[PDB]
Amino acid sequence: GVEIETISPGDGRTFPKKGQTCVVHYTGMLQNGKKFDSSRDRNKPFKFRIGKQEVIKGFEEGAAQMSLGQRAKLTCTPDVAYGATGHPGVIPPNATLIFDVELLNLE
Amino acid sequence: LVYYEGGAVCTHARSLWRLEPLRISWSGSHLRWGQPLRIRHVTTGRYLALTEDQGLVVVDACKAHTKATSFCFRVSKEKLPKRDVEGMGPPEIKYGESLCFVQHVASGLWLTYAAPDPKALRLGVLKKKAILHQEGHMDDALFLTRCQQEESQAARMIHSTAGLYNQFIKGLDSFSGKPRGSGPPAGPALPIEAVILSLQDLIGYFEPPSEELQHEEKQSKLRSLRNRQSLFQEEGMLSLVLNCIDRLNVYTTAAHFAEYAGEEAAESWKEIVNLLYELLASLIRGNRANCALFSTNLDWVVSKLDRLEASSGILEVLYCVLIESPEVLNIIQENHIKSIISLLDKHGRNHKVLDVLCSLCVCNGVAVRSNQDLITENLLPGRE
Amino acid sequence: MDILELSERLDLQRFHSHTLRLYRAVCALGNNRVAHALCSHVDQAQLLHALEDAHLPGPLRAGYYDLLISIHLESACRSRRSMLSEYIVPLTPETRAITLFPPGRRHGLPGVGVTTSLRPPHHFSPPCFVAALAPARLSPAIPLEALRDKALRMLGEAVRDGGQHARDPVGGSVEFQFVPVLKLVSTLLVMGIFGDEDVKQILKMIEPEVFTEGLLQMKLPESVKLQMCNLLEYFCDQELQHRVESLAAFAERYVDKLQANQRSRYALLMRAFTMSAAETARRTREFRSPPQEQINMLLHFKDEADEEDCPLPEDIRQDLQDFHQDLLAHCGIPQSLQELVSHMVVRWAQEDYVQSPELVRAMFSLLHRQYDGLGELLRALPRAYTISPSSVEDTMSLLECLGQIRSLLIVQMGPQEENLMIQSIGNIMNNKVFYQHPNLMRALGMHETVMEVMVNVLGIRFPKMVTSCCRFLCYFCRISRQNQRSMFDHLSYLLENSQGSTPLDVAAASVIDNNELALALQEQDLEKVVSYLAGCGLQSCPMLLAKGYPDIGWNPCGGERYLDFLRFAVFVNGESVEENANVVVRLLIRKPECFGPALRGEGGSGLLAAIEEAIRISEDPARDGPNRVHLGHAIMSFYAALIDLLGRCAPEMHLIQAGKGEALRIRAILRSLVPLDDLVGIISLPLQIPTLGKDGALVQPKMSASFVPDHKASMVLFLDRVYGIENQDFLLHVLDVGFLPDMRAAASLDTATFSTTEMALALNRYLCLAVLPLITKCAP
Amino acid sequence: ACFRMTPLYNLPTHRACNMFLESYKAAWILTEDHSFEDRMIDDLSKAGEKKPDPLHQLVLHFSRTALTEKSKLDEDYLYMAYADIMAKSCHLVSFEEKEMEKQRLLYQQSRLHTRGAAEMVLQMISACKGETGAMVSSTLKLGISILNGGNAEVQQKMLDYLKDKKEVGFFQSIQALMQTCSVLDLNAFERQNKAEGLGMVNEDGTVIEKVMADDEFTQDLFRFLQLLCEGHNNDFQNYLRTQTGNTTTINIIICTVDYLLRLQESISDFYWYYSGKDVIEEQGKRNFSKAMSVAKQVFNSLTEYIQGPCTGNQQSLAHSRLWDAVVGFLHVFAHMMMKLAQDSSQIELLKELLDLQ
């Protein structure tokens, strides 16, 4: 469902196990190439505990294959993303998202 | 059929009569007790009369033969026409004074109120029908009040506008089907130049007071404008205009109109259909009541927004309705919002459409969240 | 294209400025769910960029300043602004340290100091669009400290270059240079973001000499002047808040002395009255008056005509005299905020003929508050309450719930708003502060807010919210005797709009058991209820018409209700309210349709006959109605209620033995209104007892839809009050015809299996309330 | 209660600090007096070195709110505060001494009516549309303040304004106000009698008028009309009777007489109520005195309407049912004189009775 494409390699050794918060700075774009979010604009890294299902699914199998410091691009299909309902006013229904994710620190 | 009605009707135009003496010369003389005179309804031009079938009626102007329509105000019900005086006359009756009984001249009958108050009045409020009686009650005396020149002028403008636009409507209904073919128009000529002039005059009649008008003058003219619009609406001039729009709207373009009316008639189709849409806004602009009338025919307005013949006028009508009535905002559905947004896609980047959409969210300081959510969900996420 | 290319692309300017107006509209008045969405279309970085952008055209500079406030700050601003008129001051040591004038009599800087008034913290949530997918969403978080520092910096840059008046009007004009920044600074001041040093900076940018080029060191347009007024009103509000806080702190420090000397005085008086008596016999009135009449006695030493009457020693009186002088000096009774505003407003007015009505209104409101300071303190002290330091947590939660309730008054009702009202109102009612501190609740005016929302919903859709509001208000009224009186003034409204709980039981909650409140009904308000009763005894509910019911000639469902309010307004605390007793009788007979189909007179039916008909209608399914509502009991309820109410209006024994003419007349009128034979006959009905056996299983009749014996209780009351039991023969008649076959009906029901059947319970309550007391009275 | 009254020293601190606040506000803050209206009006009046001065921009602003076409006139505490300020401003035995006082008051009223105050007063009375309340009370008190002594300039300005605007609102609102004016009652009196009969004590509480409740407002309204025709103006004495030019006319004089008939009805109703009770108790003394003050003002208003020999008003009264009122009054007067003469404790009420006669 999620397609990880490495943009710049990290360590390839430490991967986020369950229960380690992940700090990731990111930018997100509808597959047509329009942007809905970036954390870099807000200026703060986004933290989430992997295994608590706070983030969308593809964002959670996706930031799990990445390693520490790696920068990659995820392509979450609506099945492993919001889906047929959408995030009203932000993401149209039946949408595929692309995320430029940089896993900065683990915990 | 006449009535004694109470309430706001005594600030309307259906309650206005005009005393027409039986002499053309010196017709403005001082009314004297017991002199013959017809009484004409102003907004309909129908003369009060005693017909055999229904007693008291308002008969048309072709059947007022001075036996049915003549009358005599009288002071007391005791049994008492004078020799015409070639002057303003000796003043007898006053205004807001001088209790006067109305007596038909030939039948002697006094004007009274029909006592019967049936089930419709068991819980309903009294609307005493006026009947002519042999002897009548002892409390049936009437004060005569005066109406402002604005009201009298408006009540006579309604009598001509209604006639003109009913001729227009009945002319349109003559060739509703009936294609012209390659021959002549169906029936009698449409009153097109008269309609254009009358609409132009009524749009200027209702023009909002100017801004440089100084404060107190501005607030007096606003009251007068609201009054005149209420008169026209309560006499059903916001339905005659709608009927004209509907009849002229079954035709997509001027050539479609020409296929039924004619080339010369179709030369003014777009002009007329724009003047109607301007006059409608002039009638409803600023009145919460005339704008409240559109809580049920809102789909009437929204379904005409794509029409190219007059696309700014219909949008202006919508803007007035939405900016003045808050009850209209509650009946907006996704159908309506997905249509107002489609104007942006089909008619261009027009800021007035955004103004409409802004007015759909907050009306008089209260937010309507369904409209906010619908605009957000439909307009925004496409980013187009 | 660059956005600054919109300096000459004017059509795109108009479209984009109105796009931002659309954004501000769709997120307006509390919609934080849409503010979050708009943080994906206009992000923080664009907003913070447009704040500092010098070349943005004005219509876009102002638009992007308003958009930031709308997305992030406006909801918190209004919620804070609604709490800025009530001063709940906790009795903490922090409060105790507050003094009017900074130690070492000069005014301190306005807005600079320690404030202890409770204002709930305002909540934010971070904006993220990768979170998985309903409590109300909070406003999008924006870093408030960085924003505040930027706001101060921009304001400072615009001023010391305002005086230069170069041709640098950032935004295209002085209005667009200043108004957008002043709006932001006013918002952040109101919210509470600014520290003391920042407030000092703002004050220096306003007037450097008074508070230690200023914004008054250059000529300004009438749009900037309005924002200056909105800043000075903030600093004028903080001085008032300081006065109230210092007055509360003084109360804390001074009631301690008034208590210590009262206790020591009491000790001295207790040593006295021993071998020294009858000289201090009067001086124990202070200790036996109500505590306020003691605190109202003690503070009576101002006019010098009542010096020694005040028991306070002179030292104690001195503290109050000194603080009073300080309070007067603080209120003014330039070198001061009052003098600054008083000069500057007059100077504006006499420099130009101000054309903006809003500016004139703000100007003169400020001038008024500066001249009348002591009259402003007096109009805010009604809304000042001192809570103990322990109750701070509960009060904070209660204030948050109140803020939610009064934030949904700018929103047209919907499902989610219904749910938030219900949650908030159910939360207030579960708070101990709501019970313990009734005066705070009437000072915050919750009852008025709840009635506002009930007005909006009634003026029905959304019955759940009405049921919750009318429960809250019926509880408000039971909390304390002043709450009834506060709600009693709304009786006209509730009677205009009059599950079970409905805006009528609120009206019947205001007046219940307060004979002082009963004797304040305006006869016309008793009259309108009778008008509704008339409208209920001639037609029938269209509701049941839509439920396909028999619809005979009249619904008793509304009649029963409206005979319940009229029962709580005629008979309070076990005695008859004569004044309200007579009026309802008169209004009932003047409209004799309110008595139902029976008692109609012409074409009448015996009350007994009507009840018998309702007995026979109780069983047949066709005439009872094809569930929550049945009719066989409905007509019976209506007539039982009418008989009870008519019994209530009957005069008590004082008037009857006094030979008072009106009393005898009213009793005779009621005697004529209902005969006797029907009365003792409805006493004599057969009561379908829980039938034993029936293959062994209990089959009791549903006394939610049968002749409940409680019906008869009403007619037992009437007989006692109106007809009476005067002869022994009539008594030995009623004993056989109606009474005894009921008591041994109950006694047979006393068995183990039928002890707890609901019919048995109802019959037991019936006998103990109606029959047995009458027998006890007639025993001689 | 005397056994379980709680001394303050047992109360929790907060419930004592909240009692202290109320006592302090009632005894100390409220009783404090500060004259600032004079100083404030004298600062608002001066101008700097034509354009309206600061005070004349205040009068104009409240004129603006009055002429705004709204269905009902709103609560504005700002207007109600400033109206009281301006009223206080104009409020403040030798021939010289009296004449200097008169001229000084004329100057104080000139500060206001040379800046549009009279037109504001007429506008707001018209804009209230005949609803009793606080805005109307403040407006009427302001009108009385600027018309005291029969200020001929103010009266002329008011008459000119009413005549040129030809508005029917003013007299259509005065009439409504006088119809809503309350009259003496027994029922409410009986009820409050019993309500006091309940008692004074409450559990940690103390008990706190609904008879002749708006006596102050009624006195102010009729004082306003009297001041409008003081100085024997014929134009006002005739305008009140007929409003020529206006579409409809409202005869205020016969409306005053019609109110007076209500008044004499109620006054006779107390005398009948008390004709058995040998002594009028204290409550009766208060309420009857209030009714008498209102009756004095109504009688004075009727005199001013006809004092100058305005013949039109004279026969307007003569045909009016002013005779029923006075014939009825004389009954109360004679009988209450008899009954009140029989006690010394009721000498004050008898004095008020004689003055009313």
Image (tube, coloured by chain):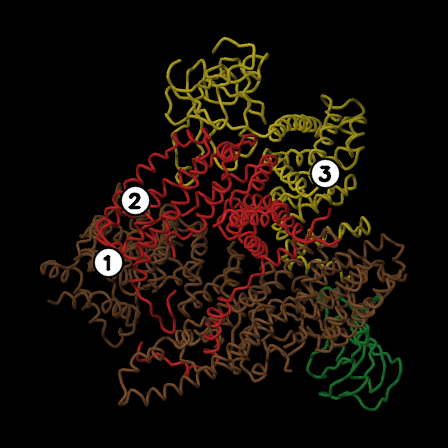
Chain colours: A green, B yellow, C brown, D red
- Amino acid type of the residue tagged 2 in the rendering: Ser
Please identify the quarter of the rendering in which residue D193 is found: bottom left
- Amino acid type of the residue tagged 1 in the rendering: Met
**Chain to which the residue tagged by mark 3 belongs:** B
Whether discs 3 and 1 lie on one chain: the answer is no
Alpha carbon separation for disc pair 1 and 2? 43 Å
Instruction: Please tell me whether residue B265 is drawn above or below residue C276 in the rendered image.
Output: above
Alpha carbon separation for disc pair 3 and 1? 69 Å
Q: Secondary structure at mark 1?
A: helix
Q: Nearer the viewer, residue C674 or C309?
A: C309
Label number found at residue D107: none
Q: Given contact means CB atoms under 8 Å apart, are the residues at marks 3 and 1 in contact?
A: no
Please identify the quarter of the rendering in which residue B137 is found: top left
Dot 1 corresponds to which residue? C715
- Amino acid type of the residue tagged 3 in the rendering: Tyr
Alpha carbon separation for disc pair 3 and 2? 66 Å
